[PDB]
């Protein structure tokens, strides 16, 4: 057995096929392009076959590179995957075709934004096959395309009963995906969900894993999830399919962040104990704790009745929603049975949680303690009592009184973020913050403006001097940038191309105090002031505009203010205290996802204190089609705005000043609609939360609300609105 220092791919190929126990392959420092590594051979427990770098952190794999393991007692470690994407189904794969890896290990890997350029082209970053493999001390962040980040596969007997160990990994940022398929960890699939996987998932740190409602999707039997930390993670740990899973000693720090969930319970024989859940704001199936209703004789890929669930000795601090018998309907009529809830501590500094949606007499309650009037009908199983808490040195709240025998065990440990991932690669912020950089004064000229844009760094601010800026070119925004007027109302912008700003990957845009006119824009349909890349967007973006005036967007028809590209997704679009006048198109066109697969173009949309005058199109066309219930948004807020002659354009097929199809949270308050088209809400699935309050409708038809997946009356809240004809 020998050490092989490998300096190029052909040198690797010369030896890759004859590796023997004890061999170690050392990749020379640098960037390797289009390197499809296969580590294979018959190692032994005393003499494994090793692959490692010359220097940890200096071997980068880019382009269409990946890694495959096949054989026994193999250990790959220390590689960095960035600036590329796998040309196969996975970046790291514990197999080589039909040949699987056993008793093998992958550690100290970094995969950082190693994304397929097509968000709809699905892939895994890590795919486990075989048995008795380990995936530890790795660092994964920034997966943006369809497909779970880490998948334990069970599509053969030699991949089931694996007892894989997934420990001490840093599962970093995953942005909101805006679609199903954004999980971080999946154990099995429905087809193989009746097999036992026995996968151990321990001591991992999940931070802002916000892909979708399922952070972890367990779809197999007898797995063990313990001592993991979920920090401001939007989603839940869902026992989706399979029976006999053990969830214990996990820690959820929501910090009141929106849509932070906990544990959802489906299927049979699960044990949920000694978990600590704090500050979780998610609701419905993304709630802090859910026990679902099942389907009688359920198909394998639907919902199986909860039976023999043992939920004991858990602590719930300011968890806003606990739901039992959830999802009850004509299909999901099977209520939980033969289950128990014991020794749980439920403390809500405020007052919110706990709701039953069906018969819950199949859940026996004992020695549960709460500070609110949680369960008055289950009187003897839940006791109301004021519990004063003290946060210990580990960061956990415990009762100050030693006579409170409820909640998680006293010695519960808390995994440290610094004990996961690797010490030689930084754990950096998910996003570049607006205005976090330097401010550059810009001369009154389009040339100097374009120059300062080109030379600015992400997070910088461009303070424009007074005067005109007549752009002849498209302004690309591929970094986080803010544009601000030295003095409000003293800066005018015009543009000759079909658009002024085009937001690319990495771009985020903030505008303040500007006047923008389309008076020099092309005499053609389809103009816009701001747009994303028409196709192929990968990174979520932010758009903020405050105290701006947009005028004369009317040289031709279909002159929008903002137009989404296909597949694009905004983390937020925020328009505060702006003036829009004389627009032939729409203001916010977020309606490109016509396939009705559950894809949408904006997570948060917020319009406040604006004035809209003579807009032929709608304020917003926000569309999410289909019957998917895996996501949180879109969210729409419209408050304290004024609309005059909005939405009556002959070309506005929605016939609405505000068109909301599939939007999941809607707040329309304290607006004035005058001589405008009405609000049109089209509710789909997921029991959307729509609220229309204290608005005035002068010469404007009352809101129209339609249920497309539910019978009878609509579920929106309409309160204190005035219709004046
Ligand atoms: Cl599978």
Image (tube, rainbow, N blue to C red):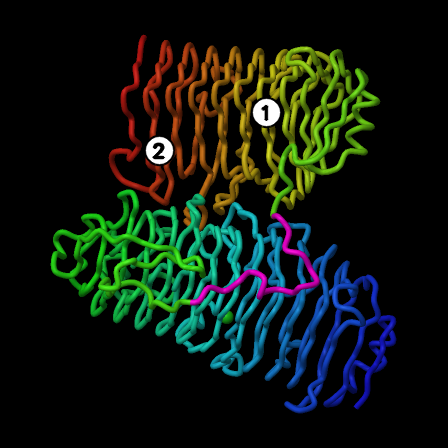
Name the quadrant of the N terminus. bottom right
Please give the label number shown on residue 690: 2
Q: Pick whichever of labels 1 and 2 is earlier in the sequence.
A: 1
Q: Is residue 44 above or below residue 561?
A: below
Rendered residue at 13%/51% (across/down) = 376
Rendered residue at 45%/36% (across/down) = 635
Rendered residue at 57%/12% (across/down) = 581
Of 374 and 707, nearer the camera is 374
Rendered residue at 87%/76% (across/down) = 11
Q: Is 269 on the left-hand or right-hand side of 254?
A: left
Name the quadrant of the C terminus. top left
Give residue 418's position: percent from left, percent from top: 59, 62
**Residue 84 on the magenta segment:** no
Q: Secondary structure at mark 2?
A: strand
**Residue 422 on the magenta segment:** yes
Q: Secondary structure at mark 1?
A: strand
Range of residues picked out in magenta: 413-429
Observer-side mark, 1 or 2, equals 1
Q: Residues within 10 Å of mark 2 (few under 14, many from 20)?
A: many
Give residue 424's position: percent from left, percent from top: 70, 63
The residue beneath circle 1 is 545
């Amino acid at each position: 057995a020998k050490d092989y220092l490998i300096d190029n791919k052909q040198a690797y190929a010369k030896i890759a096929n004859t590796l023997q126990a004890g061999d170690t392959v050392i990749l020379q420092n640098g960037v390797w392009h289009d390197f499809e590594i296969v580590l294979s051979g018959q190692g032994s427990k005393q003499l494994p076959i090793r692959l490692k770098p010359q220097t940890k952190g200096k071997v980068i794999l880019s382009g269409q590179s990946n890694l495959r393991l096949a054989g026994q007692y193999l250990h790959a470690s220390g590689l960095v995957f960035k600036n590329g994407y796998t040309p196969t189904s996975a970046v790291i794969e514990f197999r080589n075709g039909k040949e699987l890896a056993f008793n093998s290990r992958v550690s100290e890997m970094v995969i950082d934004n190693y994304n397929n350029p097509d968000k709809r082209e699905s892939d895994y970053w890590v795919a486990l096959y075989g048995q008795h493999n380990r995936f530890d001390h790795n660092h994964l962040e920034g997966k943006r395309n369809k497909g779970v980040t880490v998948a334990v596969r069970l599509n053969s007997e030699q991949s089931q009963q694996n007892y894989h160990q997934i420990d001490h990994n840093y599962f970093g940022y995953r942005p909101v995906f805006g679609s199903n398929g954004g999980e971080t960890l999946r154990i099995g699939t429905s087809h193989y969900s009746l097999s036992d996987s026995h996968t151990l998932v321990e001591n991992n740190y999940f931070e802002q894993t916000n892909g979708e409602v399922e952070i972890i999707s367990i779809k197999s039997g007898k797995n063990h999830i313990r001592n993991n930390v979920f920090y401001e993670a939007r989603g839940t740990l869902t026992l989706r399919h399979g029976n006999g899973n053990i969830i214990e000693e996990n820690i959820f720090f929501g910090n009141g962040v929106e849509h932070t969930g906990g544990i959802r319970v489906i299927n049979k024989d699960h044990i949920i104990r000694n978990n600590y859940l704090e500050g979780l704001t998610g609701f419905r199936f993304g709630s802090g704790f859910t026990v679902m209703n099942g389907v009688p004789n359920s198909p394998i890929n639907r919902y199986h009745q909860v039976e023999n669930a043992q939920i004991e000795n858990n602590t719930f601090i300011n968890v806003e929603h606990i739901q039992l018998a959830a999802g009850s309907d004509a299909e999901r009529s099977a209520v939980p049975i033969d289950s128990v809830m014991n020794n749980n501590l439920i403390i809500n500094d405020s007052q919110q949680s706990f709701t039953a949606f069906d018969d819950i007499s199949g859940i026996k309650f004992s020695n549960n303690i709460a500070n609110t009037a949680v369960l008055p009908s289950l009187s003897k199983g839940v006791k109301q009592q004021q519990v004063k808490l003290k946060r210990n040195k580990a960061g956990l709240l415990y009762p100050v009184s030693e006579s409170v025998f409820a909640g998680a065990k006293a010695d519960l440990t808390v995994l440290k973020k610094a004990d996961t991932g690797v010490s030689w690669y930084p754990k950096s912020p998910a996003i570049v913050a607006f205005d976090s950089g330097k401010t550059h004064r810009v001369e009154n000229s389009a040339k100097d403006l374009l120059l300062k844009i080109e030379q600015a760094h992400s997070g910088d601010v461009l303070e424009l001097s007074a005067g005109d800026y007549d752009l002849a070119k498209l302004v690309v925004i591929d970094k986080t940038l803010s544009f601000k007027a030295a003095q409000d109302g003293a800066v005018n912008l015009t543009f000759e191309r079909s658009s002024l700003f085009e937001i690319h990957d990495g771009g985020s845009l903030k505008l303040e105090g500007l006047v923008i006119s389309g008076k020099n824009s092309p005499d053609s349909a389809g103009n816009s002031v701001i747009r994303t890349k028409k196709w192929g967007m990968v990174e979520n973006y932010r758009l903020i505009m405050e105290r701006c005036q947009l005028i004369d967007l009317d040289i031709n028809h279909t002159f929008d203010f903002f137009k989404t590209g296909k597949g694009a997704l905004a983390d937020e679009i925020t328009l505060i205290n702006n003036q829009f006048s004389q627009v032939t198109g729409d203001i916010l066109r977020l309606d490109s996802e016509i396939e009705n697969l559950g894809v949408y173009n904006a997570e948060y949309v917020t319009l406040t204190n604006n004035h809209f005058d003579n807009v032929s199109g709608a304020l917003v066309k926000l569309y999410r089609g289909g019957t998917d219930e895996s996501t949180f948004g879109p969210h729409f807020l419209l408050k304290n705005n004024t609309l005059n002659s909005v939405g009556l354009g002959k070309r506005n097929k929605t016939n609405a000043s505000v068109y909301l199809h599939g939007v999941q949270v809607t707040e329309i308050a304290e607006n004035a609609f005058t001589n405008s088209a009405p609000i049109v809400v089209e509710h789909t699935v997921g029991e959307p939360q729509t609220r229309i309050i204290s608005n005035t409708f002068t010469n404007t038809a009352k809101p129209y609300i339609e249920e497309l997946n539910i019978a009878g009356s609509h579920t929106a809240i309409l309160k204190n609105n005035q219709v004046i004809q």
